[PDB]
Picture 1 (spheres, rainbow, N blue to C red):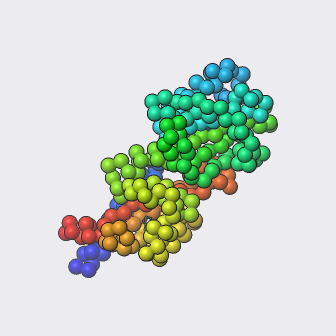
Picture 2: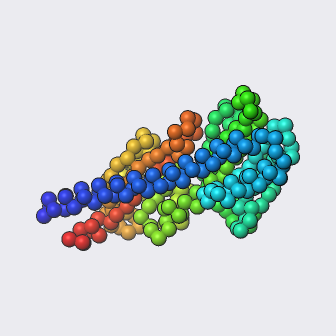
Picture 3: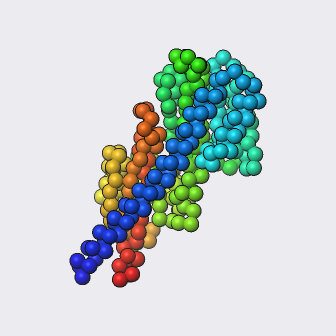
Length: 267
Ligand SMILES: c1ccc2[nH]ccc2c1
């Protein structure tokens, strides 16, 4: 019967890894589609178009990408195109943002000619609510691809991944840089490191942090500090910026849990 539990455990752990991999593929595909959409905006924005055409392109970009909460454009040679667009409930609000290029991070993207990424942060939206997310920056180029003429900044809403992570389920965690919880069913965990939340189980947490750094995947067990019951745990990393080459392209991670007692209670 000890061998019964062992074969139950193996079966459960494998199915968790299968379920988690499909979930990672779902989240990656959301990101990849947004990146593809950004790539098309990046090409179209520097062409000779009306200012209103550019604005409406950025609005439609937001409308077509449910996980984007805002977008900005900056042009070196044009003060009239230093604009930020943010979701404003049913509409999209336009705002002037003249210092948009005068920060060290925007300059980084434009000097490097490469995709750049911020760390997760809370952005104040037009209605005064805060949205947790990350900025992705791409340099805007001239048609001859040798001169950078500006920058596109895309605010990806981490909170909008509730659709994949917390909608009608509470067994998933989205984890980011150095073990920060980006999204989980328990809202109070957001922006806190797993090293703090799960300090009661340092062996399991250090193992998760090592997998996060090394870009791997694994299963393990741990005593959950909220339920006080042992859980099965599967984790899997993926490159947050995808195949795109950049020093800012680090691993995100999705974690899936199952309470051990519930597996064994079924037998
Ligand atoms: C360490 C231990 C348990 C955990 N559950 C989710 C992340 C995580 C890290």
